[PDB]
Amino acid sequence: MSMAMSQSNRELVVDFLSYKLSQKGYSWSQFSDVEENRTEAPEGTESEMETPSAINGNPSWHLADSPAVNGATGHSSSLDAREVIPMAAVKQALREAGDEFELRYRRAFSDLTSQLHITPGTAYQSFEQVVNELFRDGVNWGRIVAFFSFGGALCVESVDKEMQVLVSRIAAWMATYLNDHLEPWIQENGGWDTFVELYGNNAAAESRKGQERLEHHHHHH
């Protein structure tokens, strides 16, 4: 029992909005939607300490003689985990999947965005309705990839002109809909791994092709 998927639904909704914003040049870090890490960066945690410059009664003693592990090495080096696999193949998988969605179809994203109109005021209300129709078929794999390019493009629709006041809210909507709706079906129908094997393609750049031509069927037969 060691599952959780903490940076698999949120980190993903933000990796798609940032990747798209890159095509335009904007950056996701430019906004952040947070408070400079920590509570709100109150200038009093690191790079300042709370000691004047001497205060006897503390000549850097703190023991300084631990048994290597535990005390020094432990808690800051021991414990081998590597942070497991947070996604990686899943991220690049959505990247190439976006190119396979902006070639045919045409409609679909134009209708969803038509029933929403992202702007100063909108929220997860209307976005939850249209998105509902998207997964109303049963959370299909093609419905998840299309849902990434739908909320993604909509995000750049506001940040494209320096209007991230609503782009952050867009990432929050896809986050609750990807962990409380697309997650249960993503595991009940295989898992983010199998889906990566479906569309998430590393970069074979071959696909049973890319080799001159060989012989469609012999010219002389």
Image (cartoon, rainbow, N blue to C red):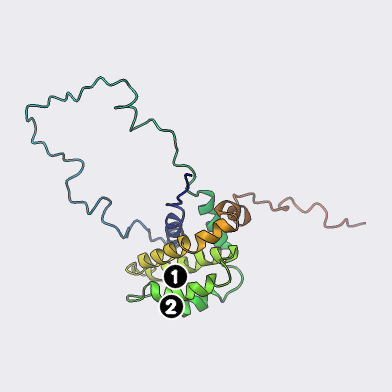
Residue farthest toward the right in the current orientation of the protein? 221
**Rendered view: 26 above or below 83:** below
For the residues bearing labels 2 and 1, Cβ distance under 8 angstroms: yes
| Camera sees residue 96 | no
- Return the residue at label 1: 154
Tell me residue 75's x, y (percent).
Answer: 33, 33
Tell me residue 179's x, y (percent).
Answer: 46, 60
Label 2 is placed on what type of residue? Leu
- The structure residue drawn at horizontal position 38% and vertical position 30%, both measured from the top left corner, is 78
Q: Residues within 10 Å of mark 1 (few under 14, many from 20)?
A: many
User: Which of the image's four quarters has the C terminus?
Assistant: bottom right
The number of callouts visible is: 2
Q: Earlier in the sequence, mark 2 or mark 1?
A: 2
Where residue 145 sits, quadrant-wise, is bottom right
Tell me residue 146's x, y (percent).
Answer: 54, 66
- Residue 221 relative to residue 93: left or right: right
- The structure residue drawn at horizontal position 53% and vertical position 52%, both measured from the top left corner, is 90
* Along the line of sight, the residue nearer the viewer: 48 or 158: 48
- The structure residue drawn at horizontal position 12% and vertical position 27%, both measured from the top left corner, is 58
Circle 1: element type: helix
Where residue 28 sits, quadrant-wise, is bottom left
Tell me residue 73's x, y (percent).
Answer: 34, 27
Residue 208 has which mark?
Answer: none
Query: Which is closer to the viewer, label 2 or label 1?
Result: 2
- The structure residue drawn at horizontal position 38% and vertical position 61%, both measured from the top left corner, is 26
**Rendered view: 62 above or below 118:** above
Residue 116 has which mark?
Answer: 2
Label 1 is placed on what type of residue? Leu
What distance separates the C-alpha of mark 2 from that of mark 1?
10 Å
| Camera sees residue 204 | yes
Circle 2: element type: loop
